Image (cartoon, coloured by chain):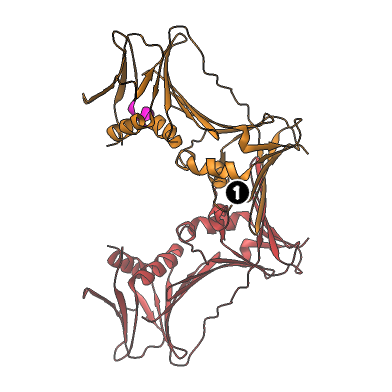
Chain colours: A orange, B red
Amino acid sequence: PPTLALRLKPYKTAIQQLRSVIRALKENTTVTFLPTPSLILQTVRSHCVSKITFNSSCLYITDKSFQPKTINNSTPLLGNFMYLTSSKDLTKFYVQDISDLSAKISMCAPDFNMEFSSACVHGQDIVRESENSAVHVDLDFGVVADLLKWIGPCPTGTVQILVHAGPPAIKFILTNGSELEFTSNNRVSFHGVKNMRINVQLKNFYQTLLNCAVTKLPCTLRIVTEHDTLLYVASRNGLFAVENFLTEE
Amino acid sequence: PPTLALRLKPYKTAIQQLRSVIRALKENTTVTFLPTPSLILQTVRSHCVSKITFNSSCLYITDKSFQPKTINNSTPLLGNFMYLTSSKDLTKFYVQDISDLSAKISMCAPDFNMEFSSACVHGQDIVRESENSAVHVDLDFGVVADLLKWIGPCPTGTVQILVHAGPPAIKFILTNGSELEFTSNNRVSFHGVKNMRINVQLKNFYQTLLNCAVTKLPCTLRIVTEHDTLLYVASRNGLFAVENFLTEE
């Protein structure tokens, strides 16, 4: 039977880094297993879609005939499935393709083993789109930390992200009139700017930053204008990538 | 294979009544499955041992060769096992005896099924002991409620239970000097009293009362003096019995 297995050392590391993100997953959150190999978490919040993709280095695949499987993370009795995989006692975690309609998940710990079969759902894949006029600014981890400390007081209202080109700058404005801005090359890196603004809910922007901050590495911000106005915020390491897509308003 | 199955209607009712108790179970809490049929939860806290026994009417047994199984409620990956059984979506729950060293638990929900095998441990059975000189007072549910409201302010210090025989009375005294007492037949029932006292931790007595109060029915208090000084507090309905054993100090 075609088996997709998690490689324990990098997976346990990754899932520990992500523990706070995984604790925050929603009722619609999906988990996708691919023969690539890949594992993808995808979550819809108001005007915000979030995707966590595990690097292939976290997985072992025995047989590429393994059919793609998407399941709900919210599991009838078990609740938050991905949270259970963050158990520090986990010794084995694999998925088997033994029926068309479902995925069979196996997990072990010292003197324990368990299996469950969850119904497959129809997933959507989300692709970061490119546009000729897009803004792209990379933020050092220290900048992300500063934004989080600033915005972290339960966050309400909106944040306006205001970008300038005259000289380059990225500016952040909150509902209460507070403003922070960055111009400085050894703190941020500008890769295409134009005079523009985007307004997003503060709660979503803060959660987005929190999720990206798990890498303790630089985060990429992009803003596009075509299908509509959208803010992309992402970070990654060699174990996983966190990507968020925030729709204006 | 010998199967012990939960009868869904009375089990789901019982487990819903007990939900708060089950949320509070400890690392040493055991779950015992018997061919009687019976299911027993047993938990050790400081000077307090608590036992929940499900009435046979909650169980169906196919084959009395089923070997007795005790397992830890704290389950490596799953965490609080009994809490998972309180899922309002549960459609099937049974235990199979297919190995000497372990119990195989199966559980279902609409489009979900799961199985796990947990290692058997060595349980102790706890028996309420009788003594010729013991105090026994039954308390109406309204009395239990009054005690809970009185003691419920996080409870610290101790409670002294002071019993009198001249005329009969049961008295409760807290560390801060507050005192409540009962003498009244249509509120409490005296079945053997003698002049005596017992002192227990307030936190344990309060938790004990909370657990018994789930029946919304009268609760039995007994106090013994032999092996040592001990307070027994219990309540039951046709679905389960809650029993607690509090050692003096």
Residue A241 shown left or right of residue B150 in the figure: right
- Name the one closer to the observer, B70 or A54: A54
Span of residues in magenta: A201-206
Q: Dot 1 lies on which element?
A: loop
Q: Residues within 10 Å of mark 1 (few under 14, many from 20)?
A: some
Figure quadrant of the C terminus of chain A: top left
- Name the one closer to the observer, A38 or B42: A38
Residue A35 shown left or right of residue A124 in the figure: right
Q: Is residue B236 above or below residue B192?
A: above
- The residue type indicated by label 1 comes to Leu
Q: Mark 1 falls within which chain?
A: B
Q: Position of residue B160 (x, y in %)?
A: 30, 80
Please report the residue visible at 56 percent of the width from the left and 61 percent of the height from the top: B73
Pointer 1: what residue?
Answer: B90
Task: Using the rendered view, name the quadrant where residue A2 is placed.
Answer: top right
- The reply to whether the magenta stretch includes residue A94 is no
Q: Is residue B180 above or below residue B24?
A: below
Res A173 visible: no
Residue A227 shown left or right of residue B99 in the figure: left
